[PDB]
Image (cartoon, rainbow, N blue to C red):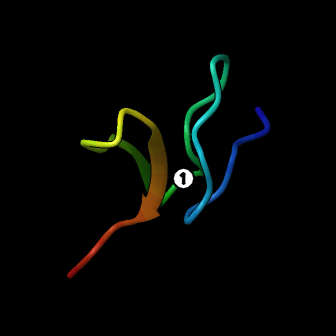
Amino acid sequence: AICTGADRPCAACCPCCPGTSCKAESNGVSYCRKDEP
């Protein structure tokens, strides 16, 4: 299925692309961010 993309704001339907993960922040909004080492 289509995904959002790292460094981008998650969406209601949709999870982050394969490799990036959705993570909420203190500001209240959540954005995707590529995995880290």
Q: Quadrant of residue 25?
A: top left
Q: Secondary structure at mark 1?
A: loop
Q: Residue at x 56, y 65 (%)?
A: 7
Residue 24 in the image: state x and y as whole percent: 33, 38
Residue 2 in the image: state x and y as whole percent: 79, 38
Residue sitting at the far bottom = 37
Q: Residue at x 63, y 18 (%)?
A: 12
Q: Quadrant of residue 28?
A: top left
User: Where 13 sits versus 9, above or below?
Assistant: above
- Front-most of 17 and 29? 29
Residue 11 in the image: state x and y as whole percent: 64, 30
- Front-most of 29 and 32? 29
User: Where 13 sits versus 37, above or below?
Assistant: above
Residue sitting at the far right = 2
Q: Is residue 4 left or right of residue 33?
A: right
What is the quadrant of the C terminus in the image? bottom left
- Front-most of 31 and 27? 27
Q: Is residue 12 left or right of residue 31?
A: right
User: Where 1 sits versus 21, above or below?
Assistant: above
Q: Crowding at label 1, few (<14), some or many (≥20) Cα neighbours within 10 Å?
A: few
Q: Is residue 36 left or right of residue 3?
A: left
Q: Quadrant of residue 13?
A: top right
- Residue type at mark 1 is Pro
User: Where 6 sits versus 32, above or below?
Assistant: below
* Residue holding disc 1: 18
What is the quadrant of the N terminus in the image? top right
Q: State the count of labels.
A: 1
Residue sitting at the far top = 13
